[PDB]
Amino acid sequence: GRVTADGKHIQKFSETARVPFYDKTQKHFDILDEQEIAGEKPVRMWVKRFIKRLSLVDPAKHPQKKQDNKWKRRKEGIATFIEQKNGSYYFNVVTNNGCTSFHLWHKPDNFDQEKLEGIQNGEKLDCWVRDSRYQKAFQEIPENDPDGWECK
Image (cartoon, rainbow, N blue to C red):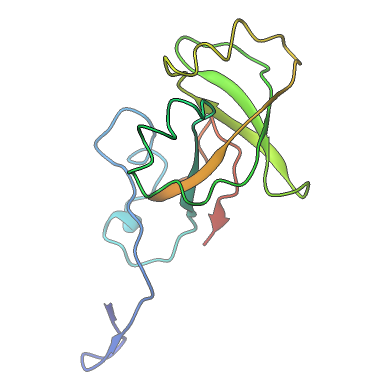
């Protein structure tokens, strides 16, 4: 909540979202002003709500990992690769049936490391999607994910 102009009333908020400080992945104590640390001026943030997670390897998860009861919402998936990094692999997935396709990164697992053999810069392959919990909000956007972050 928040107290109003007079000292007799409290207005109610809707929900919360955490913002990382005291870390070495963003810059908040050098972009924000001094008045905003006391928190008395509404500023814009980018709320994130759910992250796309994948498990492409189906045979190593159906008879030994279907006790998770979380992967009840697998729909489809297409995937590619455009840039190689130290430990993760690029992917581009379509959302439901051909409405929106965007990017993600995935840590390749030992049951999925047999699905990639060195991906060409544009070669195609299937995918498997899921949307998992997330509750955060940054200043501008992360420099690694151009996902749908709602401006609030």
